[PDB]
Image 1 (tube, chains in turn cyan, red):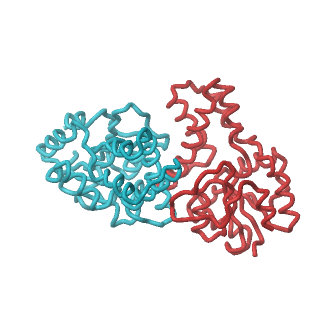
Image 2: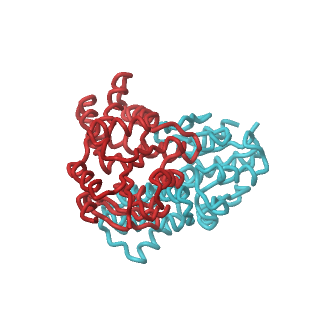
Length: 220
Length: 220
């Protein structure tokens, strides 16, 4: 019996493809190439920094990842362009079904929370901009723990804040690596696989695999 | 004053491009595509498994990564092909200058060791096959620590086995992420950048950047 739901932010509720536009507007033609690398370095820097115990918040990791991407592509990223592209993450667009689904889940009397790598500021900005702030009971950031996902200390944070046991909290994630972690932690996991990717080969299998949040609403 | 040198194995002393051949022989035309993904999942699985505290040796991680790669490309990887491709890693070919350089470093009275993610069996096979076994004082595997690089517990292992303080051990690595870790640990680091890549954006900078081991020999 689930009483709450924890959602990953970037790539699950909000689409990061929105960034490719701003990237191509700054570096015409290469927008897709920049965004692709940026996304990869962003994740890599959070994983590697947590392992070396050298933490910096998501915004710093994002700035560092962009600086590496441009330097790696030979692109001259000036100060203002840097700030501009990085500000794009504060205006992501929610996936089409996201807004209506959040309302229905909430209406069913479910506790809804966000467990993201983003800083408390980032998370706030993104959800408020999309005007979805009111539909969330908790907006959790990994920041207080000074470590990123998939470190169990991050997941534990969701269990504490919601005041429920992990077995009554559903974990919804688009990244198969994130779902693997939460599954290892003990959260019953729902994987949102819209693009038909395959799960990671790290010993885990989600409890549910759906194509969008729509299937989640109908799970209740 | 350096008294010993720790070397990363896969990609630093021995070339993993040797695998692309066996891959293309099994799946003609797609050999490069398979190898590329395989290498990436291999590293990802070691990082993610260490973070979830769900360790399996390098050989297992390698088998799992190949199984994901083929399933992800739509390729039918049968049991025998699986074993065959995986056995390729036990026969990698050392970079051209590697053999002669190892002899000169050793001749200079330097303690030489290998600190690799590979299993004790893997490491042994690879170096013995190339006939370089005798040029190494220690062949260290992360296995005993039950965790992979860049976890500091892995690096500490090199400092203990060589019986020297980290400041007298030179760390030679081709992967900029590996060099970042060893640099954080305290090892004076030499990065072997043959293909002109850029260093990672994780706060570190190697002490030396060279194009091959040749420059290392001339460093003494």
